[PDB]
Image (cartoon, chains in turn orange, red):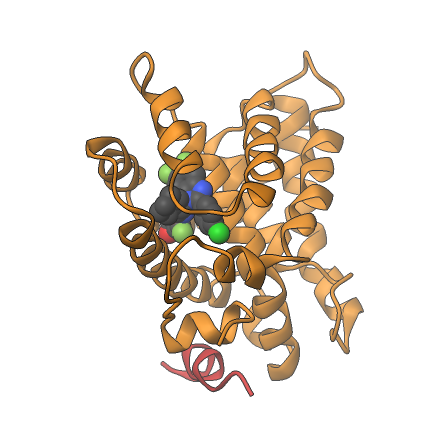
Length: 230
Length: 12
Ligand SMILES: O=C(O)c1cc(F)c(NC(=O)[C@H](C2CCCCC2)n2c(-c3ccc(Cl)cc3)nc3cc(F)c(F)cc32)c(F)c1
């Protein structure tokens, strides 16, 4: 019932590629340092989000078997998951342990960053729900890989090929949820639960950026391609 | 047409 040699291998490979990530401290210090204007925060968001896409493409190309997929499906999988992965990474960083009152300050600073009021509540409740699961670094890494490798995505021609790649990650995640958290047998199901709720941020992702309380909404060409902006 | 994304995937 414990991780097979192949599953230990899959895991370590996923964890190393996921570790190529931007340092979470960098992000949270900057936000906690001073209270920036909605305009400075929009710019920080656009730069953080463009770099995120760049890092996501690299992590994705390294996902076992991703390179073997149809080129157009490769684009639809990345385009279909990029926003979700950014929200999942934002969720992770939100629940990263900080000194007393810092998490409350980080929350208040994000709350007054320039994002429209209509997006605030669903965004923070997802961040808190991820937190209530006290997810490990290997869970965030596997969940990101599972999110990218989702076959039930609009425009995927060969879903079965995507199913073949998502299944070993689902199996590894399940085993980790049973070996490392036997007190909560529902843990794997609850992680799969968060994934369905991650999909709710895609409906109005472009509007999240367009309603930012700034006079001008400038984006990078890469962001324009991933977000449905400009 | 996702030209940038296609480039980032097809490079190396
Ligand atoms: O590459 C990465 O590793 C990476 C990339 C990213 F893009 C982000 N995200 C951000 O920077 C923005 C900031 C950006 C500056 C303003 C405050 C939010 N951000 C959002 C948010 C809110 C709304 C939207 Cl539309 C998108 C994102 N929620 C956050 C919760 C947090 F705990 C936090 F620390 C930052 C958070 C990230 F955290 C990590």
